[PDB]
Image: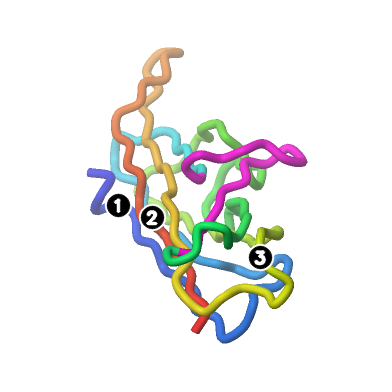
Amino acid sequence: DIDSAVRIIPVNYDSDPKLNSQLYTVEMTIPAGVSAVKIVPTDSLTSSGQQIGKLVNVNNPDQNMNYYIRKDSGAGKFMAGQKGSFSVKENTSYTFSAIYTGGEYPNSGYSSGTYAGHLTVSFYSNDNKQRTEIATKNFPVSTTIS
């Protein structure tokens, strides 16, 4: 059950995020039977070897924040921003962070409001050299500027 395995925790800011700031975090425990995980922003683009996603101001489509996903705990071979799945340990917990890398905003900076998007998480089994996707969900994610 992927819905019950994953939680998203937005970060709320009182001013514009800074380079390397965390926009939201992700926590999950791997269910029994899951061998690998993919975690990638929806609609990402490759830049500097990373899958860059956007959080878009829900009121003003011209304002958005770029970010990549960094793994902050849990064993396995995950390169920050990667698109592929990586092998995980069942019944153990993983945490990830959305890390700000830049964005589109007018000269006055970001407007107050919610900046939203989606994050794809997929679970796989790997049975005898065949990787099989067994669950996937595009989770709503956000950050806010007060």
- Which badge, 3 or 2, is on the more N-terminal residue? 2
- Above/below status of 123 relative to 54: above
Which label sits in the foreground, 3 or 1?
A: 3
- State the image coordinates of residue 55 (x, y, percent, origin top left): 52, 58
Query: In what element is the residue under mark 3?
Result: loop
Mark 2 is surrounded, within 10 Å at the Cα level, by few (under 14), some (14 to 19) or many (20 or more) other residues, namely: some
Q: Residue furthest right?
A: 48
Q: Which residue is mark 2?
A: 28
- Which badge, 1 or 2, is on the more N-terminal residue? 1
Residue at horizontal 36%, vertical 21%?
Answer: 132
Residue placed most toward the observer, 57 or 12: 57
Residue at horizontal 55%, vertical 60%?
Answer: 97
Q: Residue furthest top?
A: 129
- State the image coordinates of residue 95 (x, y, percent, origin top left): 49, 59
Residue at horizontal 61%, vertical 73%?
Answer: 110
Q: Is residue 62 magenta?
A: no
What's the mark number on residue 48?
A: none
Q: Is residue 54 magenta?
A: yes
Label 1 to label 2: alpha-carbon separation? 5 Å
Q: Which residue is mark 3?
A: 105
Verify CB contact (< 8 Å) between mark 3 and mark 1. no
Q: Which residue is mark 1?
A: 5
- State the image coordinates of residue 15 (x, y, percent, origin top left): 62, 83
Q: Amino acid at mark 2?
A: Met
- Which badge, 3 or 1, is on the more N-terminal residue? 1
Residue at horizontal 58%, vertical 53%?
Answer: 71
- Above/below status of 132 relative to 78: above
Q: Amino acid at mark 1?
A: Ala
Label 3 to label 2: alpha-carbon separation? 32 Å
Q: Which residues are magenta?
A: 41-57
Relative side of 38 to 132, left or right = right
